[PDB]
Length: 145
Length: 148
Image (cartoon, rainbow over all chains, first blue to last red; front, side, top):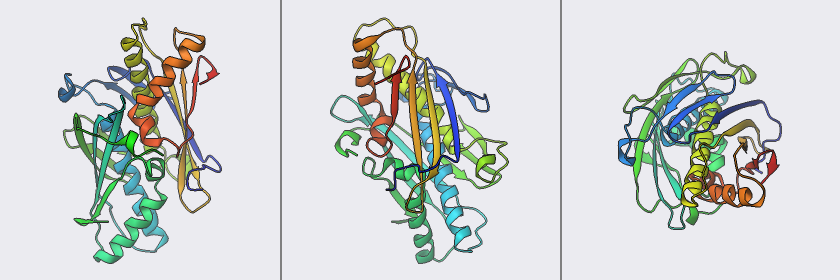
């Protein structure tokens, strides 16, 4: 099954107590941030927020996954720029939902690029986490997957 | 998974970020509110000098879930001054050639027993990160040391 972490290779942890409006940090204090509401949600937009954090994390994870598959395919790829776009809105059941698009730009003939990025979307742990909940809109060199 | 409980019916807020990861990677939001360097952790072949997506997920989920608890408490007019949440995020191989995350959310709150179970249970239904991972990650939620 694509969901079971069968053996933990790396573990981290973080604590927050003021939700979207205060501090959050990894317990080892390696990553420490102030959070605030964006202007769109009535805030100052003076700091980051969980949607941005998810965008940054997923872009990074997906980029890493593409570079991983490239390595395994012995395809020299210097960079794998990924732009992640994350939205939030109400789900109509009283909760909230995320929407995600991922746009990868890769220096390979398009069918080869599609093959790499398609495999990467299978192996990426953020993709595995959200599969079936978020229909992630993935494109490669401007073409929809 | 439940696609309907994760339908964004009207976007309140949208944001973008672009990563050129690997090592030594960088990632930035389009508005520059967040600019970070990236590293693989030492446990996964890297230098662990900068941040990584599991840290980013831990921070995001801890904050989102703390907020969800505060949100429901407010709706319930249950006085909470704060809602401490520790999110623990692990990564390892799945059986199929990819990787999967494990998540635990430990709330440490001034409310107890079945009232607390009820409140944090609602929070876990409302929280957008919880809706995003439902069924895929068996998120291990606890309140004051006790399973949800």
